[PDB]
Amino acid sequence: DNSSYFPVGQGPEINDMATWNGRLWMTTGNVQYLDYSGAAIVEAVPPAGELPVGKQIPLLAGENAPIELTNAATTCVPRYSNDGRRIFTYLTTAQSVIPVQACNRAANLARSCWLLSNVYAEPALQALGDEVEDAFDTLTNSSFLDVAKS
Amino acid sequence: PISADFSEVENAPSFLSLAENTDEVLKPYTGLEIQTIITNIVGDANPNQSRIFDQDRLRGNQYSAGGLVTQNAVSAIPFTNLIPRTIRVGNILVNSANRLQITETNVSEYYSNPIIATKLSEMISDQVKNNQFSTWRRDNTSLQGFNAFDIATINTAILPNGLSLESMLLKLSLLHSIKAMNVDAASINRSQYQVIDHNTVPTIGAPAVVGVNNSPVFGEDCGGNNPVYPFGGGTGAIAFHVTLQTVPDERKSYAIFVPPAILQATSDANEALALFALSMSEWPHALYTVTKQTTDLAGANAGQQVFIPTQSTIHIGGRRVLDLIIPRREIAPNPTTLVAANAMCMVRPQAGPDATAGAIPLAAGQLFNMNFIGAPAFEEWPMTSYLYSWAGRFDITTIRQYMGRLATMVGVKDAYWAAHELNVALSQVAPKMTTAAGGWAAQAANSAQQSDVCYSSLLTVTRSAANFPLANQPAADMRVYDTDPATWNKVALGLATAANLVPEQSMDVPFVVGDARASFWERLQAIPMCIAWTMYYHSRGITTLAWDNAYTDNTNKWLQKMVRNTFSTTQSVGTIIPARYGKIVCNLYKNMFHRAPAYVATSVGGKELHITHFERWLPGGTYANVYSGAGAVVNCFSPVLIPDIWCQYFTAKLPLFAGAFPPAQGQNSTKGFNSKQGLMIHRNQNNNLVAPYLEKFADNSSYFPVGQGPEINDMATWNGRLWMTTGNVQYLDYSGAAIVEAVPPAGELPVGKQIPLLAGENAPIELTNAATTCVPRYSNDGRRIFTYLTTAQSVIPVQACNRAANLARSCWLLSNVYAEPALQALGDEVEDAFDTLTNSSFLDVAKSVAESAGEVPATKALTDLQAVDVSSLPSTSDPSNVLSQPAPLMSPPT
Amino acid sequence: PISADFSEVENAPSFLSLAENTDEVLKPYTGLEIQTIITNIVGDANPNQSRIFDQDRLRGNQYSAGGLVTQNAVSAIPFTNLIPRTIRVGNILVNSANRLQITETNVSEYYSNPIIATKLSEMISDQVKNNQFSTWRRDNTSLQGFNAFDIATINTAILPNGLSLESMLLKLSLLHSIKAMNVDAASINRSQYQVIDHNTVPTIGAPAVVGVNNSPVFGEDCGGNNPVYPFGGGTGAIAFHVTLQTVPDERKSYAIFVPPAILQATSDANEALALFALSMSEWPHALYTVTKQTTDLAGANAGQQVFIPTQSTIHIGGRRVLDLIIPRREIAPNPTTLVAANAMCMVRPQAGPDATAGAIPLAAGQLFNMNFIGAPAFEEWPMTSYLYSWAGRFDITTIRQYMGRLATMVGVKDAYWAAHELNVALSQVAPKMTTAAGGWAAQAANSAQQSDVCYSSLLTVTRSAANFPLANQPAADMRVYDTDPATWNKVALGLATAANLVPEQSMDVPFVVGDARASFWERLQAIPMCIAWTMYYHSRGITTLAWDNAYTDNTNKWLQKMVRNTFSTTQSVGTIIPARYGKIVCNLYKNMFHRAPAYVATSVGGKELHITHFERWLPGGTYANVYSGAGAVVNCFSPVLIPDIWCQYFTAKLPLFAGAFPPAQGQNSTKGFNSKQGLMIHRNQNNNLVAPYLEKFADNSSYFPVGQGPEINDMATWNGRLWMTTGNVQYLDYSGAAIVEAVPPAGELPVGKQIPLLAGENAPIELTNAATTCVPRYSNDGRRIFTYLTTAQSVIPVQACNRAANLARSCWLLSNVYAEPALQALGDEVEDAFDTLTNSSFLDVAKSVAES
């Protein structure tokens, strides 16, 4: 509310939730990137409603291309302009009603997702080197173990 | 609320639980409960900054029965007050083919809070009695610029009833409701112009223009520049008097004083006089008009549409002619000469800034020629023309200050709020529904069906049958209190007081009275009213044709009772008594919204009872019914006005039979009640008709026994909704015979009104915008009605009642929230720094005035000393007391 | 107080601290001690004239922002009561082209302090009860001169209402302030004849003459020889009676007894009678006209010139016809023949020396033929004619005698003082300021803008729209109580008394009356009133349109409540209830001057309530607005009338946002408040717009939330003054777009009125003679207003607020303010030896000042 321009010596601060809301405004198909007053910023802007999206490669039989925003970047929410202005994500009023109620927990916004569950393994190897005992490694174990240290 | 799972609908409250008497205190319904859900504005905002021109719809995502999701789906706000007099047709705007709506009121005297004479009156009587020792006719009794012989006659023969002020406050609120259209287009809903005309589009840039007597068709202009009353067809008369003597004998009893306390502003006071005169003559004095620029759906063709406010067509009967008795500027001998009079009138009345024709023509700004004894001739003006001239000059902001001074004389908070409740109840209005399979429909342009409309109570609004002025009066729709000139004269001069009349501060005036948002806010206050009346009529199954003929019929004794008890037609001890089953709807309201309706007291023998607007309607009207897609009427349903998403998304708590169908979640979808609930399936001689699990009494009543009708049972009603919501129900007799009532083309249900879409919106799908709860059960001739399905159609739903199968349904994708009340006071107000700098002084001076009603610094102990013979002063032998009701004791047998 | 250093700015009181209620009883602020501020001024260029004719002006040395010095620069006293009716144009007298100003009043009943019966009236009523026939015999009379049947009939009434004397004393104060003008020319300062007309130079040699009905234009003469009421027209009526038996019924209850105490109050009883008759009829009875010889600025074009006093235009009372009852010389039954009537009365009423021509002409000094019981035809005089005869003989020392007698019969000490306050508050008047970049300006000669004027309350005066007599819809400016004839009759006969009617020693009459300096003291007493209203209006930044439209259609919620509590909206019966926010203005007055306004007690609900002229104004006026050169109206600023130095220099304490800028070129020159003070800048550099450090926004950044307006914050107002006092301020909104109010041509600020200079004086330089504190914050639209400078222009002031730079601004060299050298070759701080030798004495003076 109190910084169309950031004060010198200061810039935007970490705040996850406002960034989340910025992503919600962005992920609607029709955001507008503008000044505190609603003026255009100096930075070049995408053709309306577009977001950066991942690289195409040829398909194998049975594959499908990714749909909608399933292969896009979303988190890149601008806030600090080149000349020191804030950047705001705007929507027109009528476009604005469902998302605001979604922040108020009285409405829901549709989105796409991957249908993938979570797994994260304990580390596969301690050493940083692969190695397996052969039978001969066990036949000739102790001698190696002390000659090594020696 | 919306239900998330079948577990929630299965645990919803029973109807009888919500209709119980509730004893707790509750806050007024300000209409901001709905605002924080359908709008950007949570918390405060400036109306200019918010663009509530686009905040005029219910919006959300919808889920289909087939598994698709429709984003940005939409629904109209059902209610309105504007009536088009020029409809768009074929993209080209044209004159209306249909006559205007009308409404009637039954105004009358009733006992109010008990009334008592003040100290100032005792002092006056002692002044007279003391004056009787001297052969001098003297003027000790003058007050506030009035003649001593007038204060004497205003101090005589008080009326027990009490004082109301209600009809006054109605006329003021209706006027305000009309002038609130005059504000800029940015803060009136777009939809409000297109509830009835769905083919027009208003333009944001230009404000609406409020005129008078401009209408093109059916003689709606009431003589135009030369005016007459719209209903009586007559012309009034008004006369101003310095003193009561110049009033002709035919009407010295009807004279009203105009107290000096109004007109104390340095703001033009000649207008405040006109607005005092307007609030006591007959209403409407003319047909107001709202002209607004609009355009074609393609944006292509532009024009000026004409509208009639619903407030401007409701008839509050009263007084054609007025004698207004003006205060004197300087205490003086009565002005036998004219120059003594005019230079001594506290205000000298003159016509407002508009010309008028006909007999007694009035040039703009013309001055009234004062009446005084020995004048060459009597003078008066037609009042329709005198009011025609000021008609363009009132505005919201001046009504606010007017009522702000009016509050200082008499408390006006709770009374005004109740009058505003009557305002909303009689003026907000919605079009009849069209049956369909899908989510939208509307009647053909400029048809009779397009313009047919109903009240929040599910009663239809009557139409005129001939060109204005109307030759003949319509039946009364609702009954209101009247304001006596006599006890008005007593109360304005401090001579009398009652517990409801205690003076209040100018800040106590409720927020709607000032704001430009007020039109939108009135529009939002009528929804809970329909939700209450809807749950009422839908708890029982009685059909529209059956309510329509009920008051008289001799087929069934129960039905006659069921209608006779919903209207206010009873009395005792000379006062009105509230309708017996209106209290059910009131309780139903309090329990669902957790808010209290505004009420007013009636004194039955000194015992106060509360009347609400739920309890004061009168018999005569037709009940609300849907039309076919072709325009044919449909009788079979119970009365309906609005889609059930409104009923079920805006209540804190709800009846079980009316809950939303739960969202699909993995295996589960929707489910039905069975014999484990006490229900049982109906079967007949036919082997290809199946009816749901129903009551066990359903087995033993093809006809209801006389003295008895269908009973509340949520679960059977739920099953009836499950049979109905399949696309192919059949409405039939116990035997499978056709019922007499007209039925919809097969598989169709009533559905909400279409309006034009904004970019990015989608139309509602399937049954997302339909009414569902209107399940018929009681036929016009006394038969039950059954919902049937063929056997093969019947198998999945029955298993769904048995919890062994699931039924697909559509729903809104909306979560539940319901706020604690936004404001306690009923008035907005914020401390400024200066309010805190000057706090305590105001706090005690206020209380020192509230107790000061009818007080003067001189007390009886002082004015006794000046008296000749103190024992014979009436204040000594008659200490004053509050009058009892119906009347004070007289001639006791010792 | 003006400031020598910026240290004196930071340590100044906050506004809320002075708006706080104070308990201690204080003293009246008479113009006799305001007198000593104009005289006893610092300066070596100043000849200290002794005549009050020359002591009319604020003289002083001044110091430029560039560091030059200016000696004996001038600042005119703003107020006056004279409206010119013959403006000079082209250096010659020319008939005026502009209609006359008017004022009105809502007179009210006074139920406060209800009366008590005397034991005399008690025994009289007992005698009426027990039917004692003898006591009211036919020919019984008192030594008072009234017969007993009249007393027995006047006593029979019971009255709730008390007595006031407010409108009475007020009319006497008005006639006094008109008659004061006729005193020696040296006793009246010349600035007063050249506030509205800056091209006119009065002659000291010849006294102003006080005429009546001599005005040239717009029907002002009111018929000349045939006098008629200015307001509403018509003639009144007067009749003298020896008894209430003769007065026509339907007229009896209105007739006034005239006690012998009135008729022995002067050298000529007919004159005391005439003055009492003026005292309880309508005002003005005519339009009085001060005439004065004046000459050209070069002295080239002498002539008499006409002026209409402001006091003559206020309308009060207006009762039209009156019957007066008079004492009789002898104990005799009521007269039956005419000679038996004329010889009977204590004094036989007659016209004064001036003659009149009318349908009922009055020869000069004509005797009246007294009414009697058997009279064939009732006898009567025109009222305006009657008073017209005596209009030439009222005189301020005679009024002084009359006042000493009234003071003896009944109390007059306090009531006359409050009436005097109402007189000053209503009849003192200043022209609207013209905008400029420099020190002096005025509107073009003989123009509608030249004659626009405002009250001390910063409310514009109403102007008549048609020829006299007027026939208006009333537009009252403020309430007053009415003097009740019936209670006067109850008291004059000893039948009754009241708690404030206690008789006083004649020496206790307030010293203002009968003194020739009274006009000058009036002008002086007017200034502090403006200081309190000014500090009220300037604390919040509401524009002049937002006040002008605040009682009409264009209102808000907040403007609605805002105008509602400034004024006396409330109307309980028989009372005047004070404005809720008038109390704040009285608090400002008491804290900034350590003195108190006159009170009137008034009761509501048994609660006592003081009331002051601050609390009894009425809503619906138009506010002071600045003009552009060439006359265009501009209404962006909050309302103003007078230059800042008046405020800074008469006050003992002022709020922080109002102080004088410290002199240039010193260390601790003018600076500003920044982020630490809790403030934040609003940049808009994309459009070349940068604005000072301001209050942190509270959801009020571009539109104010409904029902709320800007908050008090001194430091932000100070910064706003710093932005304004640069030469190129720009009044825009949050986006940098234009606001609806009209705006000054760029760099202009309102500035004080020009008057001709005396020898050796200088025009004021730069911003020394200008309003500055009038900074906008709230527009009629409800939007915020911002004062912008371009990004380049805005860099030094931002460094100053940041306290890493100083700013250069002009100032008065008065009191302890000394000029600063360009170098500032500072040495070790050192107390001077003389300052230590004479320190205790300096403390003794200050202690003596604090004691008072």
Image (cartoon, coloured by chain):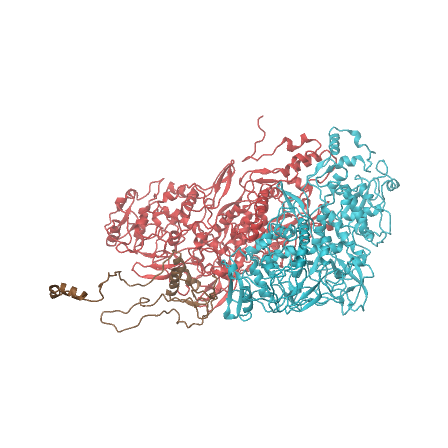
Chain colours: A brown, B red, C cyan
Percent x, y of residue C70:
69, 67
In this rendered view, identify the residue nearer to me: A96 or B519: A96
Q: Of residues C844 and C72, which is closer to you in this image? A: C844
Would residue C122 be found to the left or right of residue B701 on screen?
A: right
The quadrant holding residue C658 is bottom right
Q: Is residue B367 visible?
A: no
Residue C171 point in image, percent of width and height: 75, 50
Front residue of this view, candidates A75 and B679: A75
Quadrant for the N terminus of chain C in the image: bottom right
**Total residue callouts:** 0
| Residue C607 x/y as whole percent | 62, 42
C216 to the left or right of B711? right
Given residues B545 and C198, the one toward you in this image is C198
From the top left corner, tell me how far across and down residue B606 is, in percent: 52, 36
Image-based side of B127 in relation to B187, left or right: right
Residue lying at the far bottom of the rendered structure: A58
Residue displayed at 67% across by 30% down:
B871
Residue B534 visible from this viewpoint: yes
Residue C777 lies, with reference to residue B121, above or below; the image says below
Q: Residue B62 sits in which quadrant?
A: bottom left
